[PDB]
Amino acid sequence: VTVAGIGCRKGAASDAIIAAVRAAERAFGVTVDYLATAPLKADEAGLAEAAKGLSLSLEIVAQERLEAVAAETMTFSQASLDHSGSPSVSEAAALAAAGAGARLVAPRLVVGDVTVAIAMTSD
Amino acid sequence: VTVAGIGCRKGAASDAIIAAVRAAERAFGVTVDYLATAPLKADEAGLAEAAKGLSLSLEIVAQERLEAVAAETMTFSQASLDHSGSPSVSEAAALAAAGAGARLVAPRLVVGDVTVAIAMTSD
Image (cartoon, rainbow over the protein chains, first blue to last red):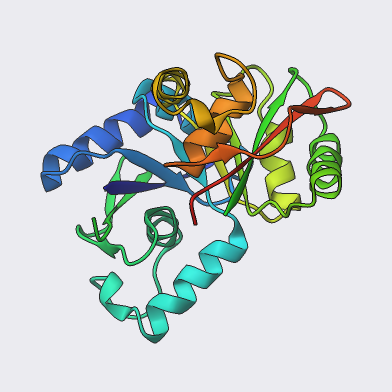
């Protein structure tokens, strides 16, 4: 199971998100079967519409859960990230939705101004 | 793990959703640790804000996944629902987010015009 964590600036078109996910799939040789995000801000419709377009489920991960995941990856689950220290918001969202013990399999990707983080889980 | 599937009419206040979830918790003797919904319609902000207020994650379950779950519960997983035939949209959302083999543990609840379906999973 592979999760794509999505971050974007307030006011992002659904087709920009869709393009970003499919570009991530091609660039990394993965196939996303689940979408994830942090608590969405002022604009929220673009991301929800893109999940519909991609025919994928979306998990809007609570801030408490994001914080927990970020804390875990800095203590004993440091093998979950492929960079130093704290995960980014999108990275922590993908890892939270992925669950235990997921890991990040690709470097942080920005396509336009949509951030895509890919995580894969144990199974 | 216990999932509450949420359905509401277009234009529902976040506090109405919150009230509905906490009333479900009290009425059934459960504690919701995960929220779920069907592809959201014209209004979408009320439900996302309520998950933030309840400090719970939300899964917006894709229509393909909802259909699959509804199909499963009418074939061999009929023990997942406590009524006859097809699950409701909220029931199928809660069961999808809950995963395999969840079951519905409480009857369909409406509080105001917010529908709440509670599912519990194997673990």
